[PDB]
Image (tube, rainbow, N blue to C red; front, side):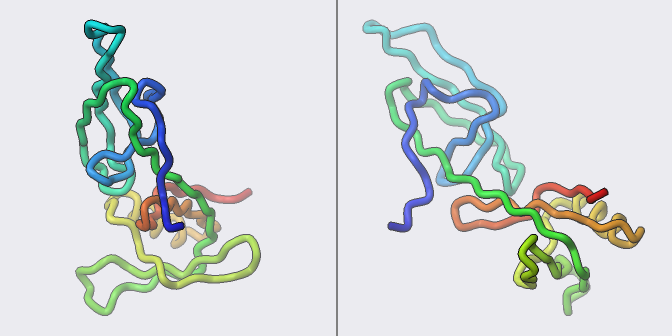
Amino acid sequence: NASKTYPMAAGALKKGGYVCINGRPCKVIDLSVSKTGKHGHAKVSIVATDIFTGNRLEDQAPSTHNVEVPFVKTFTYSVLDIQPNEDPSLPSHLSLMDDEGESREDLDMPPDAALATQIKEQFDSGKEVLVVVVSAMGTEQVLQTKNAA
């Protein structure tokens, strides 16, 4: 077993939900449904945003057709250090801590510009920075940031 999606009827999709298009894990941002066919058979039109790249994707499928929905995991870390890459122009390294006392250094900063500035600014200010790491389809990225009280 290495399977990272599950089956769902296209007609069961809602704005806000996850879907694979082009083998990419997406959140549905627009949903359109045609009336019927000749046998109650309707066509579903999906516009979804890639959760990692931010890219617009489009997909149509019959309502009875079973799309794949990605399993999405979410883990929250505290940031211990930010270290610049050896190559100044590449994304910075992150040193992170989970709630069990284990660090990990294997994750970098996100491709999101505005998100990577926000993390650097917050850390620099002396607040405890909490990054949210979302995983799906083998890819792991930082997608959110907040602080503790």
